[PDB]
């Protein structure tokens, strides 16, 4: 097994120079061996990916999936540790930069079928990972307008060269 | 019928990440003015409803203690009175349920 | 095709549906506030209103007594139905029940609702209240109303 | 008792050694030298110095001592504790995991009055910082850069605010 | 030149900000307790003269920041971006409170200020525009009013529907810009230094200095637009959602000068009104 996500919180950066932009705080948290399918957890992770901590908590509090409660607990723990240990000034000033579900260590069981035959069940377990970044959530990538789209087309036209000649 | 070929991870990703599959963001969530916890606009506040349910459970337990057994539902109205409260003229002739606590502010 | 079908298909059949609604309605009559799946509460609200009307009809009405005897599985509630609820609503003509959705059931995430008889002794529900008349929009609309009244 | 156990100790000469030990221990904190810390401070001191400073960089520097350090109180399988009052001038700058300043100024010196209690074990023992007594009348420490939120009672639904 | 006037006014505003923030060096800690109904008992150990009720809301949650328009500090209304000055009691006021009166007044003043900025920056250079005052008309009046004196060259010109629509477009451009409502409590001397080129603003500053015990005046900037505020304003122009310069009316006493009153109506994002209700509100505001 690998546990690099936990270690990711132990990296210490050198002191920043006064004439340097303030480095946003990053907090890595995870929960291991959740009795939940990673495929099902991925939908919740994608849902809360890129949102602010408060918005993610709000969505999870009212989503009906079982993994929603687990992710809410993980996010609350992440917020608490970010405030206590990672010197994050404001609780609400955090957004989910990364949220993914990983396969856990699963157990194999037997499912009995009709004619003395069987299948191999898998008591599925999954991991859950979050990175919380201090600061307002990055603005959503605006859809490319017709102006920019035509600009790209014209750039493609201009890039044309006389191929296969001097 | 059995699969004729294994579907690739590309096709599977397409199918299972199609926005029809993805969870929809809910924009009907709002803050409860009473307690400040989150609530869906049409749904009742969970925190406030739990407060009311716990107070109702206490009142109902007192009701059961006073009734003393099954099939003893009163034939008169009921009034809940808290510590430091006396029955009013309207409350006269009504079964009094006494609660050993101060009247909740929300309760009236 | 279910055009015009007004009754949900519940339980193990029509009789089981009637019995489930009867149990829910007996609980409602006993406790004056019952939380149950949303669809079942919606189905039983009409029957609760109908029992209130039958109680209004009076004790002496044999038809009302038979209806109450059928619908209230606990016979101690029939005197209640006829002497506590119907007298309470004698002034009213309808809307005896308040039904409000509740956060989904923790077990199976079922759509739940709480249904109560109005004016019960139990603590009031956190009823949803409209925005105060003193808000910006409401004050502007009050200005509209005052201007129209002054015009007329 | 100290002299009958050692036979070469000097109360008058102690303050210089105590000051040197203090400066070296704090420089070891600056450089994250736990091996030298375990020799310069006791086991009751090392956790207090290192636990909250783990995962952060401290830029500590002693600039001068205002008044000369002098022994104050000494008491005594058998340990001997010496209290030394030091009114010196130091600097601090504590940064986060991300190198963001969170306490003090890297250059501005501050006057610090403190009472360092050293201890020694009486064959191969030595004099190591054991504690720091903070007077109840001590001036408030330097304020923190970041603001703080202190949650109120996380009331359960049945509970009511008082 | 108008650009020079704006530049120098902004320069004076920035110097005043720097002086005020330097007057309190280091980080003095003040305790502000949440006296609000929800989240009771939370005490915030904030930086004096730096932290704001918006910082309090950020500590609490994002919903506070989004929904809180004003802050009652020790019972007095405060701008969400006005730095706190002492340990106190704080209560955030939203639009949907039981008695939103103060928030309504603040939003109303902010809308008037945005209207004034649009008015000043809309007209062509050759025409002189001088903002005289923003009357504190009630919300029941159905329209926030801003009083201006235009160039004598335009003494017989009335804005057309297209001109009003252009004013609305400029106001919506400001809303899209989403500028904060920077605020300062600045001495009447500095206020007069800033507004020395406007007799109306000078006399308004004099009235405010007379009303208050000291000579302290509320000076607000949206962007490159210094103005005197009758009271607290809203956090950011993005609070406004619907905004319409409804009409313009010349005041009856025209002999001294033409006091033209620009009447507009607005509604925040939190209180959006349907299209038909908004149309009726526009009709009632055009009066
Ligand atoms: Mg078999
Ligand atoms: Mg398998
Ligand atoms: Mg069924
Ligand atoms: Zn609530």
Image: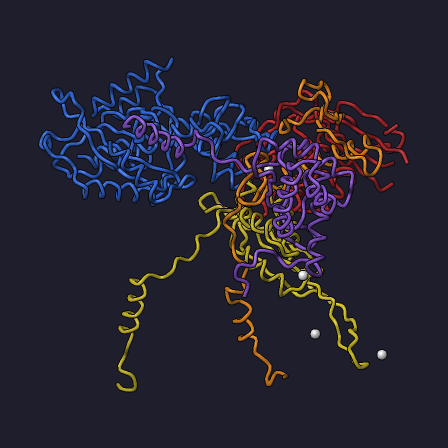
Query: At 29% across and 83% down in the image, what residue appears?
Result: A163
| Chain appearing in purple on the rendered image | C
Q: In the rendering, at what x and y percent does residue A47 appear?
A: 54, 57
Query: At 26% across and 25% down in the image, what residue appears?
Result: E133
Question: Is E212 on the left-hand or right-hand side of A47?
Answer: left
* Picture layout, residue A103 above or below residue C146: below
Q: In the rendering, at what x and y percent does residue D83 appear?
A: 76, 27
Q: In the rendering, at what x and y percent does residue E197 appear?
A: 20, 25
Q: Is residue D23 visible?
A: no
E26 or D108: nearer the viewer: E26
Q: Colour of chain D?
A: red
Q: In the rendering, at what x and y percent does residue C92 appear?
A: 57, 33
Question: Is E151 on the left-hand or right-hand side of E281?
Answer: left
Query: At 72% across and 18% down in the image, what residue appears?
Result: B84
Q: Colour of chain E?
A: blue
Which quadrant of the figure has residue E143?
top left
Q: Colour of chain A?
A: yellow
Q: Is residue E32 visible?
A: yes
């Amino acid at each position: 097994i690998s546990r690099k996500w936990e270690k990711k919180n132990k990296i210490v950066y050198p002191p920043q120079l006064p004439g340097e932009p303030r480095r946003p705080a990053e907090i890595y948290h995870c929960r291991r061996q959740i009795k939940y399918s990673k495929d099902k957890m991925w939908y919740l992770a994608k849902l809360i990916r890129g949102m602010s901590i408060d918005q993610a908590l709000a969505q999870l509090e009212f989503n009906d999936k079982k993994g929603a409660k687990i992710i809410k607990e993980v996010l609350l723990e992440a917020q608490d540790m970010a405030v206590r240990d990672h010197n994050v000034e404001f609780r609400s000033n955090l957004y989910i930069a990364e949220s993914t579900s990983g396969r856990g260590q699963c157990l194999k069981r037997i499912r009995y079928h009709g004619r003395g035959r069987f299948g191999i069940m898998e008591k599925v377990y999954c991991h859950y990972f979050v990175k919380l970044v201090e600061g307002p959530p990055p603005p959503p990538e605006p859809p490319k307008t017709a102006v920019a789209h035509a600009k790209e087309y014209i750039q493609q036209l201009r890039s044309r060269t006389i191929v296969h000649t001097l | 019928a059995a699969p004729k070929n294994r579907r690739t991870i590309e096709v599977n990703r397409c199918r299972r990440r199609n926005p029809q599959k993805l969870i929809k963001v809910k924009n009907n969530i709002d803050v409860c003015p009473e307690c400040g916890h989150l609530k869906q606009k049409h749904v009742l506040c969970a925190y406030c409803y739990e407060k009311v349910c716990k107070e109702t459970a206490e009142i109902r337990r007192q009701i059961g203690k006073q009734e003393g057994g099954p099939f003893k539902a009163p034939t008169i109205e009921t009034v809940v009175l808290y510590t430091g409260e006396t029955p009013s003229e309207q409350d006269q002739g009504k079964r009094i349920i006494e609660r050993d606590r101060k009247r909740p502010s929300w309760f009236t | 095709i279910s055009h015009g079908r007004v009754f949900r298909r519940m339980g193990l059949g029509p009789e089981s549906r009637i019995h489930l609604l009867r149990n829910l309605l007996t609980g409602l009559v006993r406790h004056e506030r019952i939380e149950a799946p949303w669809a079942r509460v919606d189905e039983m609200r009409g029957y609760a209103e109908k029992l209130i009307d039958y109680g209004k009809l009076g004790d002496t009405n044999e038809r009302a007594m038979r209806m109450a005897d059928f619908w209230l599985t606990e016979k101690d509630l029939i005197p209640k139905l006829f002497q506590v609820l119907a007298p309470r609503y004698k002034d009213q003509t309808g809307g005896y029940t308040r039904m409000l959705q509740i956060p989904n059931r923790s077990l199976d995430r079922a759509k739940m609702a709480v249904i109560e008889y109005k004016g019960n002794c139990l603590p009031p529900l956190p009823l949803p209240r409209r925005d105060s008349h003193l808000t910006l929009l409401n004050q502007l609309l009050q200005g509209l109303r005052q201007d129209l009244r002054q015009s007329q | 008792r100290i002299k009958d156990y050692d036979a070469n100790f000097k109360i008058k000469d102690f303050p210089e050694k105590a000051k040197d030990i203090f400066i070296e221990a704090h420089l070891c904190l600056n450089n994250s030298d736990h091996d030298r810390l375990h020799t310069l401070v006791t086991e009751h001191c090392f956790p207090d110095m290192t636990w909250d400073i783990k995962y952060k960089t401290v830029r500590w520097s002693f600039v001068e001592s205002l008044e000369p350090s002098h022994v104050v109180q000494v008491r005594c399988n058998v340990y001997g504790q010496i209290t030394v009052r030091m009114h010196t001038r130091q600097t601090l700058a504590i940064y986060d995991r991300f190198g963001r300043l969170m306490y003090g100024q890297e250059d501005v010196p501050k006057d610090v009055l403190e009472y360092v209690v050293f201890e020694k074990q009486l064959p191969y023992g030595s004099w190591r910082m054991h504690t720091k007594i903070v007077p109840p009348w001590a001036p408030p420490k330097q304020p923190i850069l970041k603001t703080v939120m202190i949650p109120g009672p996380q009331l359960k639904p049945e509970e009511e605010y008082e | 030149s108008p650009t020079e006037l704006t530049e120098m006014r902004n320069d004076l505003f920035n110097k005043e900000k720097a002086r005020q923030l330097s007057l309190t060096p280091r980080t003095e800690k003040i305790e502000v307790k949440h006296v609000g109904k929800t989240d009771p008992g939370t005490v915030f150990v904030m930086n004096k003269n730096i932290s704001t009720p918006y910082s309090c809301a950020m500590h609490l949650s994002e919903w506070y920041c989004r929904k809180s328009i004003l802050a009652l500090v020790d019972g007095q209304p405060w701008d969400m971006y006005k730095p706190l000055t002492k340990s106190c009691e704080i209560k955030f006021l939203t639009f949907k409170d039981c008695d939103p009166g103060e928030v309504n007044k603040a939003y109303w003043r902010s809308c008037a200020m945005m209207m004034g900025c649009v008015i000043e920056r809309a007209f062509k250079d050759e025409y002189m525009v001088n903002l005289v005052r923003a009357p504190e008309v009630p919300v029941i009046s159905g329209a926030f009013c801003y009083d201006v004196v235009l160039d004598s060259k335009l003494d017989e010109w009335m804005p057309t529907k297209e001109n009003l629509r252009s004013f609305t477009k400029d106001a919506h451009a400001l809303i899209y810009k989403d500028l904060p409502f920077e605020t300062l409590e600045v001495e009447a001397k500095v206020a007069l230094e800033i507004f020395q080129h406007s007799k109306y603003k000078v006399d308004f500053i004099e009235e405010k200095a007379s009303q208050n015990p000291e000579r302290i005046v509320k000076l607000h900037r949206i962007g490159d637009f210094i103005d005197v505020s009758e009271g607290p304003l809203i956090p950011r122009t993005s609070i406004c959602f619907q905004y319409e310069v409804s009409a313009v009316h010349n005041l009856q006493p025209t002999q001294p000068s033409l006091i033209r009153r620009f009447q507009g109506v607005s509604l925040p994002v939190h209180l959006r009104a349907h299209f038909t209700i908004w149309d009726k509100l526009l009709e009632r505001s055009r009066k």
